[PDB]
Image: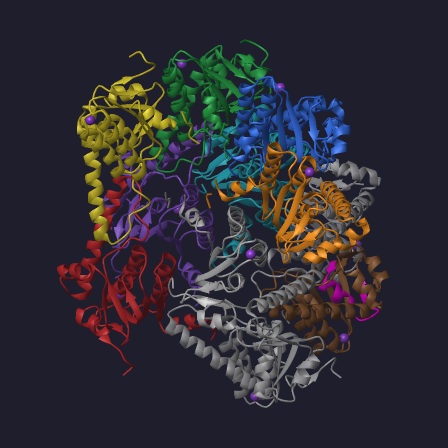
Chain colours: A cyan, B blue, C green, E yellow, F orange, G purple, H brown, J red
């Protein structure tokens, strides 16, 4: 990572925060720390949250989400490359009016998926299956609010992988505008 | 597996069938085949099903269970060593009055357990969780019938691993008699 | 590991019992095919009893059994013990209508095709296999609707995700004809 | 990790301490180190302990817990993402009145679970089993005190995994308030 | 693991049934050859029934079967059950003209050669093997065109990528002669 | 070799071997032979040769209960070693007919779990209680075999307790040491 | 591992040189994105020089670079050294027209998408991803024809299998503008 | 690790030294180094040795032990989380009157345990077994001294894993006081 | 190969029994089984025990040794290739006057060797160390009897690996005669 | 890393650049970066390119090659240890008159060889085989120019591994001089 | 490693050098470097060599040894934890009068043992065996000198692992004093 301060610290001075690659507890909390830092520095200026991510941990994603809503500054979001699953959730969670994507950005939404497995007694599996259903509806309810859409639409549209171009994500109500250039 | 015909084939002549170790499709179906053969040889004579098993695949176990109930001969069961989970299920499914255990046998019952995992979309996990709940109730319903007990008792008593001595397994209704030796 | 009585399975073959146990593979499928052809050669006039306890497996391997069941003269009667899932359920439902059975606690499950591993190569190649996979899905829903005397749309709906059935539900759906409880019956 | 002091060293100036991911000897003692440092800097000002953790080592968690109660400053806790198991324990252990959660936080409590193994003579397994029961009761007693509930309630409610929304954790007595934004602080 | 009646496969061999099942290797191919030679020896005039359920495999192993089929006096009739892909499809189409069949739900697939992991060595060595692979590719397209009574240009066009065919499509192409639903055609 | 193989031939002389770790398969093979020999002649003695370090408790119990269940006297002979469940089965031979060759090694001890107990504390409690029941059951049965007190067995099996053939005789685990057919 | 003079790459960054070397990954691509945004912030009026030696990589990762190249005000001039293949060649061809270069012995290669690993799931899921892969394939061909000022049909033809081009062929093809032999 | 001078070094200014995790040659010698350093900076002020450790190498633990006793300053000990095996030995080795534990600390003592195996000729195994007995006796004698207890008690009480709460450890004589807060 | 019987079955007719390679429970009990069977065939005729072995499990070896002394037939031993450790023990255990070696045989004796290792509690290590020394002493005592030498001779000569030619072995008391051919 | 600035950074002040070990994209680009840097510092002073390398990626090598020819300063090359394949190519690409080797340096040239394989359809394999032949011709053509030798000679002399002493490399036209010391 | 300067650099200011863990080429040469550095800093002041080591490479150990004797400053040694094999050799090599141990130190001496194995032609095995015997003899000669004891005594006392307490080591002549505290 080049020095100019390193490049990401330098862009952090312009209130740029990056989310890149898989969302983990660590990648997410680093984002949380930067958001808290920028608010501390100036609680009134917008923050620009750049997202290129296939998603990842739900709880990790929520920590970012709740922080975006908790802090005073508006968090504007920009998708480059892709925003899939939790990536798309966060992209859409940006301050309404300030959710953007670059022209060839890819957005994808879907229902939760467990990689690996559920292992234990039937009683335990029942408890975790019920929790997974609450997570699924919870995510559909929040996502519908972000998109100003009916919940029933989100349930229908996330049953399987739903790929959207930037215009489709805009029309869906997931982002507000496509930016081609600063004009 | 020493010759005398191997030892197990020789014992098959005496209408003895063994279930030893994990219940798998292959081990279960080998039992089914032996049950059908003995019925073919003589549909009226009792079959002696010796069980020493920690259990295994539920559907593999059901194939034995359904074959035991379908064939004409009485299937007598004997627990030696242990009968746990599907093993105990099969032990308890032997012809009423003809379910036995040796004095130091271990019986154990419990609710279904998935080793490994449920992996995929939530929709699939919901489907498979519901199927699992169905299996759990079905097994409790069938087990309560075998033991001549309340459904609620089996539900209570299989929530966690429940180990029973031969005498406790008798008291519960899981077997009919403890055999110390051929003398009664 | 197999008792001699002939080995036990060769012995039951004398009674025209044929087993399909575990994953359906080329080798396991062709072994079934061979037993079908053998029993036909021995006596084309007698029924064959095809016992199925299987989670399925290879679709083409399964097809080789299916077409063989339809090709030979003897009625191939099917019986589910333990389970018949996917290609296993397909074969069960493909038994001579009127002679498709299940034991009471059998589990049947049907669903659309699923690929193990993956498709890797150029987009062109992937397009082709995807297009092919879609045909398989369609063909199987068609054949399955015929087996069940059900409308195609019903099968499409009911196979989108894993669909577990008890023997009675499988009977109601039209996959089997009878549930067998015990031997005490028709001589 | 971005520099501004690195970002975490920077937030430490504001008496923010993070617990992120599994609780290990090393991750827990780093928390311990920071708590003692903040106390040294100013023994009278509140410390803000932000927790996003699935839990981990009980003895590692206990080192943090005992340090939280030991130092002069109030340790305020905030759950973001999740607080499960020992994570949930530590969240509930914050100074009463200053335990918070973000709205979509996930909280979970349960009895101790150990795997890997218990290996040895029966005598050794007996000693460790009795100790495990001792640990189980201790944690339930401490948790009941944190939640202002009867011990019997905690025993019932941790027998299997018990997931709580932020609101439920509040009703339970595990946290005091749910914060949506900086205008949310009440009581 | 194989029932006794002789074993099941030996029993079917008395009826001149020969199986090719699964991947074509030197050992699986030579077993077919041994059986072909044996059945010729038992009776050089009666047809042989070659059942193919195969995804293909080794080209040289497949060729040993092919040359043997053409070398012996008896007609070799072929039947696809399940699938005949790649070299499997080649052998299916190589059956005696008029005697090539498929069951209704059989799958046929043809394509150009695909090479083992990789080829490794000096550029000179690589050139020699690439030339050979090109000679192999054309050779197979030509023989296949003959089997199907088709133009070489068509086989070249139709095998550039994986080409899946139903039994009827394989019939229309000229790869097999008839589809057998049951013992009646 | 192939004399029939050698073990089948000796089975005709009513010799049954237990060699190596006691597993479900090895134990049940022993059980089948016992039942076979009883079926051939329920009244003549069976000779059970044991060279074993022990193994599965439940597998061992299937042998033990079969030995007591069948009509024939089961005579036991230790060669090489009989440890743990191996020693248990040895001591279980028909009283008066339990033997060891002179340089046999006998060892007794309390149960030990290899690998681990893994799960919830409730489950671990359940299995710890079961293992303790096994420990006591085996000490009582061993006390009966040896005509010794339960308290002695508890004391003498706390750790690995190695015994010579003479020590094993004095303890009451075997009846006689055989050096050759005379004696 | 990296000489200091500030490290060597930070040093060349002062001359507005940004490197893309090796596989294009999310992290390697976004580091480029960071450097583009930084240089713009330092001087929105001066050219940026993007040196590419890459076999390609993630399509989405590449687009993030691509869209950022087009979004920022400074002209992003591109230079191929060693090679630019697949997404590497795409990015090379995306440089500001008139300022796309290659060194004389550079290798360019273009082709249709290739799938890493495999497709795993239900036929429904497989259909969705194949339809998506086909969209990407057409999208890339359309953009590439535009970069090269060529007909859409030409790129479709010329990318069906691996297509190697020398510097001159890439120039003739319209992928680059000039070949640089010597600084003088 | 947080900078403030990094956090652990910062606490070193307050004469706080940590032992965390398994005792190894490297982790033990780092503690020895800090102890020697603190003595050199000020030989007259107490050192605070915070212990959260399951134990580890005996000789490594002994290098820490002998250094605690060698240096002029009092080494006060505090258990947080746990002190087991060599960890408990070191905890109990703090200057008498200055050994503490936090309330929910877990303390455990036992006899030596060998990892891996003893392998070689019987002559060599004899030598190493004799050495292990001296090690065992030596540690029980040193522990009996630390705890103001009879040697006979330590031998009996370390035969198998012996778990203690902080209060039980105070009562046993392993530590002097339990600290709940800065007031205790 | 088969001969009219596998080749080893055929030689059993000659009353030839082989021990070849490492002595394990399974290999040792297969020898035991052959000895017992040859005794039942004819308790009066000599058995010829051919040993080519590096040794192995002490208990497994002792099962062979005790069986050799137990059965009625004389057991002649012949070393071909090598007889080392328990191999050498069994060789020197042949009926006195009837222990042989071929001319280029390698014989080696030493003290017990544990490859692997004592792990666990110091109490347990002490028990097993005590046991090892007993085994060490008993083997030296028995070997001294075999060789018609005193215990101290054997202690000294087994402290480390001690290789012997056939002739040295004879001089030592370990075998009776070297056989060049069938003279 | 010995510090003085690490040692290599310090030598970069002397306009010394090293190529050591396998030529990879990263190691080659590091060289490219250093060449561009030195040119920026002083476009008129010679650069000294020290090579100890068995070769590696051809496209990686070409990026160095083209950079050496593109920049204004003369790039002098020195072989120490060895220069084989792409290493030898780069050594011979130094400014004519300024290509050197130390007395016991090893040079080796050869035709391209593929590590791993050509795997895919025959169509894809034909494409890549043709390209390999183009690479082979281009490298022989460039090498003949560097060496001032006939194309037919390089084709001949690289059919198999061709090892050269420093003197042989000089005679061949691959380098200009052998340096024993600064005199 | 904490900062104060890392902790070990800080103690170097007090002329403390550590040998901790296995002696390797790298760990030994780091000791050599510090010994040379402390000597250059002040050739007249004592150096304090703290040893906690189980030994290791013989040639690596010798590099420390010869350096200790080569440099002008006295190298005082202190054992903490353990000094075994080469560790004990180096401890015993401290300036006479200045070799110390902490009270619960463990000292161990023994003859050379080979890591891995000796593998190759018989000729090569002979060469390396001869070499190992010279090393064994030299190590015993030097150790005899350090300890002011007869060579024959060291030969006897190193034949197998020889464990010593601090007092036994003082008595043996391996160290000069036991330090309980700075008194
Ligand atoms: K906000
Ligand atoms: K029945
Ligand atoms: K039919
Ligand atoms: K506090
Ligand atoms: K022919
Ligand atoms: K009996
Ligand atoms: K631009
Ligand atoms: K002190
Ligand atoms: K004898
Ligand atoms: K130049
Ligand atoms: K000196």
Residue at x 25% of width, y 65% of height: J108
Residue C186, position as x, y percentages in the image: 55, 9
Residue C26, position as x, y percentages in the image: 40, 30
Residue at x 54% of width, y 31% of height: B10
Who is closer to the viewer here, G25 or B182? B182
> Can residue H121 be seen here?
no
> Which corner quadrant of the image does residue H182 belong to?
bottom right
Q: In the rendered structure, does residue E157 fall within the stretch colored magenta? A: no
Ligand 4 quadrant in view: bottom right
Residue J110, position as x, y percentages in the image: 23, 60
> Which corner quadrant of the image does residue E171 belong to?
top left
Residue B22, position as x, y percentages in the image: 59, 35
Is residue A18 found left or right of G25 in the rendered image? right
B67 shown above or below A50: above
Who is closer to the viewer here, J106 or C147? C147
A181 shown above or below E103: below
Who is closer to the viewer here, C179 or J134? C179
Who is closer to the viewer here, H177 or F104? F104
Is residue J44 found left or right of C62 in the rendered image? left
Is residue H170 found left or right of F92 in the rendered image? right
> Can residue J32 be seen here?
yes
Q: In the rendered structure, does residue H89 fall within the stretch colored magenta? A: yes
Q: Which residues are magenta?
A: H82-100
> Which corner quadrant of the image does residue B120 belong to?
top right
């Amino acid at each position: 990572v080049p020095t100019v301060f390193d490049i990401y610290s330098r862009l952090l001075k312009e209130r740029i925060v990056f989310l890149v690659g898989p969302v983990t507890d660590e990648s997410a909390n680093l984002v949380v720390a930067q958001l808290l830092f920028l608010e501390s520095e100036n609680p009134d200026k917008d923050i620009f949250f750049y997202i290129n991510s296939p998603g990842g941990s739900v709880t990790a994603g929520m920590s970012i989400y709740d922080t975006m809503n908790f802090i005073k500054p508006d968090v504007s979001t920009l998708c480059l490359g892709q925003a899939a699953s939790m990536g798309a959730f966060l992209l859409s969670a940006g301050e309404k009016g300030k959710r953007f994507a670059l022209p060839n950005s890819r957005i994808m939404i879907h229902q939760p998926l467990i990689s690996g497995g559920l292992g234990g007694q039937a009683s335990d599996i029942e408890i975790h299956a019920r929790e997974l259903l609450k997570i699924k509806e919870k995510l559909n309810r929040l996502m519908a609010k972000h998109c100003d859409r009916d919940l029933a639409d989100l349930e229908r549209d996330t049953d399987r992988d739903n790929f959207m171009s930037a215009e489709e994500a805009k029309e869906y109500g997931l982002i507000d505008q496509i930016l081609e250039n600063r004009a």
